[PDB]
Length: 581
Image 1 (tube, rainbow, N blue to C red):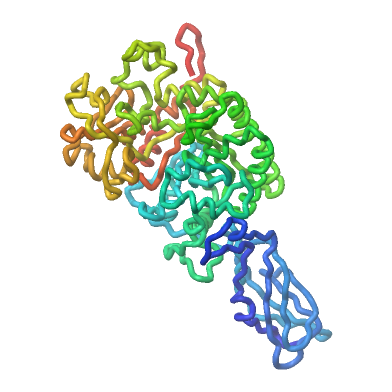
Image 2 (image 1 turned 45 degrees about the vertical axis):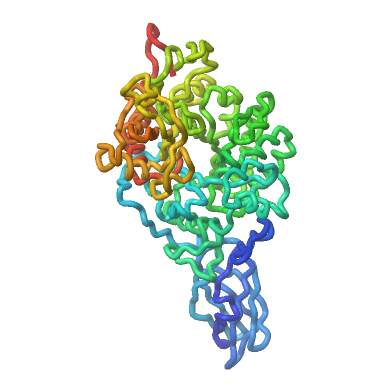
């Protein structure tokens, strides 16, 4: 028998290999920064200085032969390819006429984007998040935002993952027309231009590669030599901890929806769909795709865009085509992929799409049952209410009434129930609808008591402007505030109201508010009570479950209430009553 091979650690790259190459110290185009290989190139060097060397070498991973070849001299480099990520016990064997001798086992690491090479993520969750035994068939979704790792200081390990079934990652941009991005700030448009250099229009890219895969997180044990870092590596480790969790990339959103309006041309859909397939093959931890087109028919960030004739049909076609593509991935991998979308719930948004047609291809519709009222104007109202509030005029709820100027309402009022009922009215099944919960408030200032028609209901007042404040209090953009900020600075420990604010609740609407009479500051949000109501409502209607925007803004109260709401209606048996969904 020849001399047992001795592995040259330095010459074998310390046995660290990767199916993906990611630029860590530079920023350029997505295709320049990211290279994915179906087979990792393995290169291992071993030495046989003393004694004989032998004729043939064999390389084993956990006892299974993965490479073989001839031995020449005292030095042999074993170069081969391997397609499965993970950790393996590697042995190298040398053979001749007299027999074989094996090296001692040593661990080889082959990185892949499923996280197979990673240990389960260590969590650091706010203990205010309680423990629940909610049926795993019930959807409990939330959005994690890429940029939350900056000022918001909210990282993947902070997510109450055991209280979630779906994590939607916001947001994946589409290269092309993106003038709406300029409204964001922080040089975000420039970043997108850079990402899209070398990328064709209508293909997806990563907006912020630093946050996505470059940034070293010490809680995840990231190093210089770590082939994948950032949010993505942490999400990979999270999948190792929670294999049944669904992590889905969210494409678009409010300021990244511009390219969607060019999807009336099927060629652009084709380009997009192909890029998504490539994206899902490259980033294996993702379990499907979420489409947040805001909005088919118009009413989005770009005022000059929207086609009420063609957008809805295009949206439907997009879902059909994405489902075909996902079926291909399912055939190729044996995995199951989900197709979802977050949609507007105003009557004027819903009427622009035949969701009965679209939903046959989809797993879930995330109904954006929030942003009903807000700081964009000076009219108070419940931003995320289940039902029509006390402040509403006669016939406003159903839309058959008349406004202040004698002008008829053009459709039903913006409420969660009105939206859900319109979707059910189209023929969308309840069990594919997911009800939206707000982890944020919208707000005004200058709603002083003198402006109120009903002295005890600030929703009957008039504002002078948007809510202002500091990021310490959860105000990241004027008119919007983190739920945890509302709790810490307006509500206090038991909703007593602090710092000049008083707590109020509209039992008709199922909607809370805080109101400071002196400053006229008014905030509309979801609280424990309203979320309990939403949960009860979702269970009664047989909805798929609940989802939320955005997890970083919760202190645990909202997600807790989501679970407790789903904890606390039989088929129709008889006529002679109000038939209703």
